[PDB]
Image (cartoon, coloured by chain):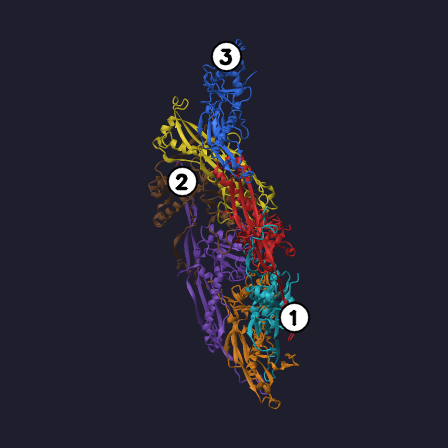
Chain colours: A orange, B purple, C brown, D yellow, E red, F cyan, G blue
């Protein structure tokens, strides 16, 4: 018996190589594209906004004292932060596998862009963390909730609250799961609100485009006129550098790869952004 | 450690200046544009309307004396009122900030026109306050309210009460807060009345354009044929003047900025306007 | 102080006169248009109708006396009544105010034509008054009312009662308020029977044109085939002539304006008209 | 004093004559239009109609005896009955009123065809009366009624019972009032089953033409294949003859007008006609 | 046009000229195709066949009436004829649908048809809901259903189904409902017993073979006849029902 | 008696032969077409996929140590299995029935391909069996189930779970039995969400094509982006060879027919496939 | 060609082309108020089959036509029965004896003969505003009548010397066996009640029949269908010959 087992003639057949590497789910970036992309060259930004406009204009009787109106201002600061991470690899591995170099680069950019988007949306606003949209966003009005309101009614309300600043909304940010449980809403009769089982509804709600991102926490929603309520300032575009002489890399026969970026998030009109919690 | 800290070498870096002052939300003016416009150059206005038309036109018997009809007239007057306000600023701020005056000018106009619109609607009528639409408007008929009516029905009822003057309506004034809860109405099944979540309904109701304005008090509505019920008469347009010698301004090294305007609201047909209140 | 007050220099500024007199609401005249229009040069009208048709036609046995049928007739008369009214005015007022002349004319004509419509619909028939559509109209058959009928069903029933005399109905006449409450009917769900809030329903129901007129008493409705049931006969069109020699007039420098008209309403088929009362 | 009343010169005014006469509601003739029409020339008509078809057709074994099946029909006879009536009028009237006769003719023909339609539908069958559709008609199957059926369901049921004889139903005969109370049916939610308030529905039910004649008694209904099952035989068409020599007419200046007609109703397939009563 | 949707039309119509018909169908396909270990013995598959026969049966009936009525009344002559055809064709279905299969009776559909799945019945189903289930059971043979057979009585109450709202399911009173269900034609036959229903892919699962068309003949001189001055009318027909796919037909009971 | 049975002249008439054979129900092959059909020429396959991407990208303080990120890989193998079966028939049968040869071929193919599909879906994975989709697929997230969900709701949930891998779904796989009970879903009123007893609904759900095959187990269901999550590699196409000299087939006048095939199933992204159970 | 008058000849002969007929009779008359009735005359068939053998029929052409004539006569004798004593029920014709008015016994004179009774009946014919036509008797009865003598010996009817054919009181006599033994009938058949012939007496044959084909026998049949109508039931009188 001359089989193709290991302990036989099987050591003659070489398994076919599948050209290429299998990359996991490539998340579609959104948050960054929702804002204005301007670039700077300094470590901070200073914009000026009208604080308190005490308008006392009124009807004045003939030959009488007219009303006095006062205005207030403020200098708002927006610091630039830095995001980055490095990978220490074997100088040997890099030579034995050429395509690895180009791969690591494309993978470090995505890896960075993720925690970038994660900042733009949920920036703690503390020490180094950026002042993310959700930290700035004016809290949702708990009074807009009426008897028997669907989860969809809430977002509808949110959209209005944006108008309380005389500004049109741009889009809606929801966690994919929440968006899901919403499209599957039914009426007291049993029917489907968005679309019959015959076809999955498009990503639109109340005329406004919907943006489902895993970056958005579960049970948290954000609505506003992002297209011009805040803008991102690029001090330095994300780039990848490599050093052979870094530390003891020359001695351990290693290679250090770096991928960094410098961002600065400015929040012009916080009244045009709303964050809330899906009470359920 | 030569960092960018405040106590270190972080003094050479100057934050990038972002040009332009950030103006808040600009409330879209409407009430002014609704009413017919015309101007005068007098202190007041005098129009005459048919008061009491005693119509006794009846069937007359042959060889008999016919009926006598009478027509009464009245002289109605509409006084011109003045609206204004001033800002006492410092000369220091004025010279050190060039584009400031230019800003205040294009700011006081809005601040004034805001009260202008606020007057035309909720005009007190007492003293120097204008006799706004809500004061003149014939009160809503509580009798029209039937058991099981939504806020949408009430407005529909009002549109009819306007017809009792043989004049068709042309607009519906509502507080954005209320207009919202109306657009988001549901039936027993659960479906939306104005439009499914797929898209937001346009600002129209019963064939008549809806005008949502923050100038309209919450829980108050106004309907009528404004385009032919009342007319605004402008004596003097919004003007801005500055004075260096006003009072002790010369000594205190100050500068006063004034912004005034002269109006006159006439109400030809009060029966063509209605004011109401939602009881809920 | 030199103010615009009365007890001051306010005597030099004369209020601007607004050209034009403000007429009240002019009711859109109908009814007279629903009926056929003919002209006459006599003082009365005589037409003939089949009174009683005694049809005894039946099956006849061989060699037997047959049934004798009989027919009765009648001479129906429609007298010509005169409607008018006059107005006595001072020669001063008429000369000092030129436009007044032509104004009074356009007012008496309306005031006259108003009572004209008022007769055609609710004519007492008492001597001088015309026999209006309602005094003639065949009463609604209460037996048609089923359990749980809406005010809309009632009209539908009425329309049929006309067919019960082999005659097609022309239109429906109701008080504006009633027509309103009708158009705003809802089902056990909430949907609008005639039209969702999007737009107001057209003045049409059950294929027949609806005619809302303040001339129609509240709670009263009149359905029928007016186009081929009744006819209006004009002896003399509405004319307006003035004279200042009428009695005292010349010696008191007065002016008497007259506005007369001669009519005659004929009711050919009273069975084709229906009047009734809604259940409160 | 010179009026238009009797006392004065009112004698000079002669009322305007209205050319023409007013005929009452001319009922639209049907029923006989639903049946097959044929001409004859006999005093009666001996025919036959399949009563019982004993079908014994079955699978036959080879060299075996075939099944004997017979068709038993009864020999029914359709007698020729005569319908008519006459009018004894004054000769003075006939000469003074020219077109009077022409009227009476077209008037008696109507009265005749009217009581004719009354026979074809509800013919007693006793003596001189014909065997009307409702007499011959096979009773409705009460077992077809189910829990919670509407009047509309019943007719639908009947239509099926017509198929028991295997013959497509020609139409549905109902009393105008019943047909009415049917068109105005609503579902358990409110919506209109037929046309809605917007427009009246056509006289069609279950694809079959509906015939609403006052000839049909209230609460009674008839469904079947009229255009196939039964046939009308015209011995003598409806004609009108006049004679002033009849009896003692010549001696009293009288004119006797006769309107006669000879008929004969046959029923080929009685199983194809259903009659019933609406239980309320 | 009273096409009661002839039950025959639902089946393939072919002509023959012999005593009977013989077709071959695959009985048992023993499929053992499976994964095979290297250098090992493979699975042996097998196939079974059968020579299924469909006999040609004869259907007919006769009547005897006086000649003085036939040759004397011509339009009646053809009447009796056209009635015997209807009478025969009516019993024709009677076999095609409920054939005993024994003796001379044809092997009817219901006899062959695979039983209905009593488990498919869910809590709170309509009558039409069940028929829908049947349409699926037909798919257990990889064949699109072709038609639905029902008793006029049952079918009647079917088209009159209503929702908890009030409206009709098959059609608002404005117009009559056409004989169709889930896109499948429906045949109302008195031949189909009440409470019984038949569904399947008739279009290509069973075929009817006509040996002799329904013909009517008369005999002036048959036995007695000549003496009794009578006449014997005969309406015969020769059929043969073949059943290719039995799994493609369903029979059940409206448990309600 | 001269009949046509055995004991008579029935042997003279030969039964009519029906052309060819009647093949049973041929199941529709689907699964194989849902995947990528690749070609090979080896014994096995080696593809590399990124395992654990330890992304530690974060916001770094000035002049501070950066976050170290790491990446992990793996070499996944896909073995080539062999599927086949043979059938030895009598030499006689083959020569006496020419149509048989080509028939057996067509049957062995359908028989093989049938067990092929039976592997691709529910491949055990152990021994020589392939690693079928179901044994690879990620289990359905029970958490996604909300109170009051239909079977159709669950499938909708699965479609989302696919997106949780940043990949769009391709189709739905269900046992016709379960799929059936789904198309027959009704609302609280009783209407069919898909059909409505007029026409059978198409095999499409939520915009995605539905695939009902007996290959899928009862109660089990699979959803994912098949046309990209996996790939089938063919080493040897389905071929049928005939041997007459196989062992003692020469001496027994036999003939063996073989039908072999070589496959290899690869599972690139298991996260893009879901499997579950309908608890009910 | 039997030289004898037929009851068929007595009545008026006409043709028809219908299933039945709608004619009108005459009941009573109180001489006023006359009575009439719209009656029906059904066209019923009559005939009698005769079967022999083809071995004889094919071996004699002269005998062929012979039987045809022997049956035509055999038919008339049966046809005569349907006309006279016709039951008028199932497949029987509206008979004469059934429709005929009974004899008036109050017309018999004590001392007359058997023939005198016949003369009395001829008179009752006039009592209907009609003229008499003929007499129908039983051969045996009619025989005894022709052979009558008085108390002395002389012939009542008349000697063979100046004898002729079948007449009595100047009227045709039809001696039929269909007439019961001791019964008679008189009427104005010539213009009273007549017969309408739908189909004349035709003859057809068939080798295939009840047996025939297997027995080699052949069946012969003379089918004839007609209708008998009675216009004046008063113009006919049937009576019982009392003896």
Q: Are marks 2 and 1 on the same chain?
A: no
Position of the C terminus of chain G, as image quadrant, is top right
- Judging depth in this view, the residue of C123 and F172 nearest the camera is F172
Task: Name the outermost residue toward the bottom.
Answer: A251
> Which mark, by number, is residue E151?
none
Which residue lies under the disc numbered 2? C231
Nearest to the observer: residue F210 or residue C42:
F210
The verdict on a common chain for dots 3 and 1 is no
Q: Position of residue A206 (x, y in %)?
A: 53, 63
Which labelled disc corresponds to residue G155?
A: 3
Distance between mark 3 and mark 1 Cα atoms: 135 Å
Q: Secondary structure at mark 3?
A: loop
Residue F189 visible (yes or no): no
Query: Counting other residues with Cα less than 10 Å from the Cα at mark 3, is it few (<14), some (14-19), or many (20 or more)?
Result: few
> Is residue F41 visible in this depiction of the protein?
yes
Q: Which residue is mark 1?
A: F124
Marks 2, 3: nearer the viewer: 3
Give the image location of residue E227, x and y in percent: 53, 35
Q: Nearer the viewer, residue G191 or A12?
A: G191
Residue F140 lies, in percent from the top left, at 63, 67
Q: Name the one closer to the observer, B77 or E70.
A: E70
Distance CA(mark 2)–CA(mark 3)? 108 Å
**Which chain letter matches label 2?**
C
Left/right placement of residue D98 relative to residue A4 reads left
Which of labels 3 and 1 is toward the front?
3
């Amino acid at each position: 018996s001359l089989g193709s087992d290991a302990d036989s003639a099987g050591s003659l057949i070489q398994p076919m190589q599948i050209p290429g590497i299998i990359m996991p789910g490539l998340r579609r970036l959104t948050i960054r594209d929702l804002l204005a992309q301007g670039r700077t060259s300094s470590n901070a930004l200073e914009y000026v906004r009208e604080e308190v406009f005490t308008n006392n204009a009124d009807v004045v009787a003939e030959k009488a004292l007219k009303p006095e109106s006062d205005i207030t201002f403020s200098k708002q600061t927006a610091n630039v932060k830095t995001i980055a991470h490095w990978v220490q690899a074997s100088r040997q591995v890099m030579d034995d596998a050429p395509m690895l170099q180009s791969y690591i680069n494309n993978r470090l950019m995505y890896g960075l862009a993720l925690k970038e988007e994660g900042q733009l949306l949920n920036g703690d606003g503390t020490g180094d963390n950026l002042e993310g949209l959700n930290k700035v966003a004016t809290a949702y009005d708990t009074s807009l909730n009426a008897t028997g309101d669907t989860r969809a009614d809430i977002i509808a309300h949110a959209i209005y609250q944006v108008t309380e600043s005389e500004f049109s909304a741009s889009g809606i940010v929801l966690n994919p799961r929440d968006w899901h449980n919403i499209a599957l809403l039914k009426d007291n009769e049993g029917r489907y609100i968005f679309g019959g089982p015959q076809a999955f509804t498009s990503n639109i709600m109340w005329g406004l485009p919907v943006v489902p991102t895993k970056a958005q926490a579960a049970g948290t929603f954000t609505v506003g006129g992002f297209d011009m309520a805040s803008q991102v300032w690029d001090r330095m575009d994300a780039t990848v550098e490599v050093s052979r002489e870094d530390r003891d890399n020359f001695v351990k026969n290693m290679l250090t790869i770096l991928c960094e970026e410098r961002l600065a998030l400015a929040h012009y009109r916080p009244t045009a952004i709303i964050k809330g919690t899906f009470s359920s």
